[PDB]
Amino acid sequence: NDIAHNLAQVRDKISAAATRCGRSPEEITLLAVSKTKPASAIAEAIDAGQRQFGENYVQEGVDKIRHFQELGVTGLEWHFIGPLQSNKSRLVAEHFDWCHTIDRLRIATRLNDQRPAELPPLNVLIQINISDENSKSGIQLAELDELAAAVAELPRLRLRGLMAIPAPESEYVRQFEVARQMAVAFAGLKTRYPHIDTLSLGMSDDMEAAIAAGSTMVRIGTAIFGA
Image 1 (tube, helix red, strand yellow):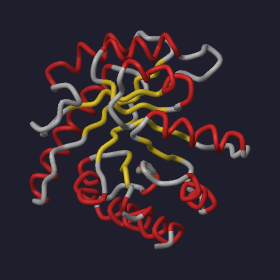
Image 2 (image 1 turned 30 degrees about the horizontal axis):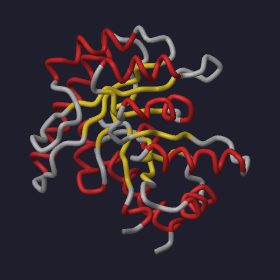
Image 3 (image 1 turned 135 degrees about the vertical axis):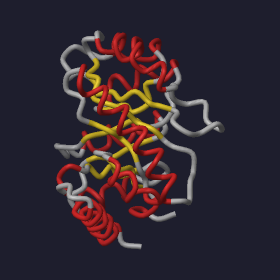
């Protein structure tokens, strides 16, 4: 396919979905999910104006980060959106700008400790397992207040909101209901904690329900880079 054309098509759908439910299209960040795609494909996306990329595997993501740092491309934002094992946390703390997958205090404390002080604080989301019994990633909502309080004190992290990967769901009604559960948790978090502004929620198949429910960031891979 053509990455530049796909990017425009995805941005159009995001913009339409926001407009339909009265939201401004600027409220929704497109996170281009480049896992398993070569740097040359990311390079095409960059040449077409895309600046935020999400990677699922640490060494793959760090190799790409270094590649575009050495080319001297600036303005990029790299999000780690895969599960994080403790033996790979240092590479994430030293190179990524965001991490969506905080689901236990020890991994956040490791990231905090391994983040150099000269870098900006690592932007982190707490991941909720909202509806997926087949996943072991993410916390239950009942554990959120406690974990958020603990994570919030880490000086080299910045708690920015929540992420979830709901169980696959074909019914729009259930897509919206599950997404609203996350939006409701997001809003409650936003009242007490400072600078809560990111709800990472939604991919191609549930994009409309996620945006209608209150997502601020959709994660799109196949529809941009192909399969």
